[PDB]
Image (cartoon, helix red, strand yellow):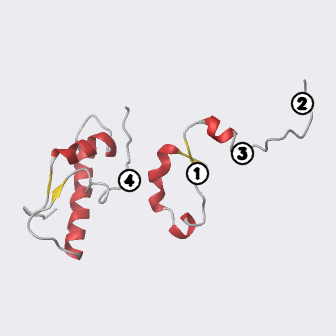
Amino acid sequence: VLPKDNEAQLEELPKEVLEGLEIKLVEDVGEVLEYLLLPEPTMPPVV
Amino acid sequence: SGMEGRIEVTDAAILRVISEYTREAGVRGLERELGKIARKGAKFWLEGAWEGLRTIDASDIPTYLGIPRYRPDK
């Protein structure tokens, strides 16, 4: 997960690595926080 | 850069440079970006040469630069 303005930083990345890395681009924290969580809750909270 | 009258930018390329590919209140980095244009054009010439002139709009700039270095304070 890499920021949106870093999309044109990718040209020095090796293509053999660039073909190995499913790079996602993001604009906002709300894009990340529904991308990385598992939707169910596991542990009880504090409250 | 040793070039002659065989490649030229319009001011569409100048708008492309000022819009994306530089950010400064001076002309040193603009000089360096135009040097990048001249060196990429000279190497692309000496590998495979075109004929006469070659006009550079905003289409030919990302084929020579690709990489923004100072993204501007829009």
> Label 3 neighbourhood size at 10 Å, few (<14), some (14-19), many (20+)?
few
Q: Secondary structure at mark 4?
A: loop
Q: Give the alpha-carbon distance from disc 1 to disc 3, as whole Å.
A: 12 Å
Q: Chain of mark 4?
A: B
Q: Are discs 1 and 4 located on one and the same chain?
A: no
Q: Quick one: quadrant of the C terminus of chain B?
A: top left
Q: Give the alpha-carbon distance from disc 4 to disc 2, as whole Å.
A: 46 Å
Label 4 or label 2, whichever lies nearer to me, is 2
- Which residue is pictured at 51% across the width and 44% down the height? A4
Q: Secondary structure at mark 1?
A: loop
Indicate whether A29 appears above or below B13: above
Q: Give the alpha-carbon distance from disc 2 to disc 1, as whole Å.
A: 31 Å
Q: Secondary structure at mark 3?
A: loop
On the image, the x and y values in percent for residue B21 come to 32, 46
> Label 2 neighbourhood size at 10 Å, few (<14), some (14-19), many (20+)?
few
First of labels 1, 3 by sequence position = 1
What residue would you read off at disc 4?
A: B67
Do the CB atoms of the residues marked 1 and 3 lie less than 8 Å apart? Answer: no
Q: Chain of mark 2?
A: A
What residue would you read off at disc 1?
A: A24
The foreground one among A22 and B33 is A22
What residue would you read off at disc 2?
A: A45
Q: Are discs 3 and 4 located on one and the same chain?
A: no
